[PDB]
Amino acid sequence: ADTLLILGDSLSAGYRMSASAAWPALLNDKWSKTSVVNASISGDTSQQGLARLPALLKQHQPRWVLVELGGNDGLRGFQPQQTEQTLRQILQDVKAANAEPLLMQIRLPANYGRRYNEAFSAIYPKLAKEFDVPLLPFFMEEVYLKPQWMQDDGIHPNRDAQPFIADWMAKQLQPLVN
């Protein structure tokens, strides 16, 4: 069975819940034909993710790598330019390992105004085109529309949301994982 490696942060690792409760575990249960390895860690910045990538690629030899990073690069001393370069390196390493990188669009809180959010968000479409890879929509967009699926911080999805996200991801990934 082929392997899908998820390289992400709290949105994929699960925030204040076990890994077994996070959507990647639910997706894995739904998928036998395709193994889903959740290499996500809460709090991770794109840089911390890239630092773990080499070992993950060599160990799991994934066919597809879902990159869901950048959201934490808000308070780490990095500017959109840095986050962009870091993600660029990730996509390169993925392709170099003969794996198909799947980039997910990330969007920042509305309480950040124009300029910075537009700049941060613009990074993903740019890279997706540069490497000619799939650019998945930010799944949290649909979750925000359901207050009952959001944790208190108004940032992370709760336990009740995971099943929905798993289904959403299955549908989005299905065509990509063939």
Image (spheres, rainbow, N blue to C red):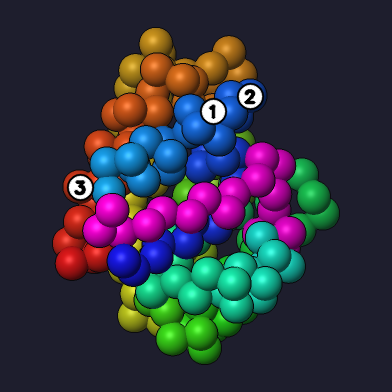
* Residue 137 in sight in this render: yes
Magenta span contains residue 76: no
The amino acid pointed to by label 1 is His
Observer-nearest of 159 and 148: 159
| Residue name at image x 66 percent, y 60 percent | 49
Give the percent coordinates (x, y) of residue 121. 49, 54
Q: Which residue is mark 2?
A: 16
* Residue range of the region highlighted in magenta in the rendering: 32-48
Task: Choose top left, top right, bottom left or bottom right for residue 168.
Answer: top left
SS state under label 3 = helix
Q: Which residue is mark 1?
A: 156
| Residue name at image x 57 percent, y 81 percent | 93
Q: Where the C terminus falls, by quadrant?
A: bottom left
Calculate the distance from the C-alpha at mark 3 to the C-alpha at mark 1.
21 Å
Q: Is residue 58 above or below residue 160?
A: below
Q: Which residue is mark 3?
A: 171
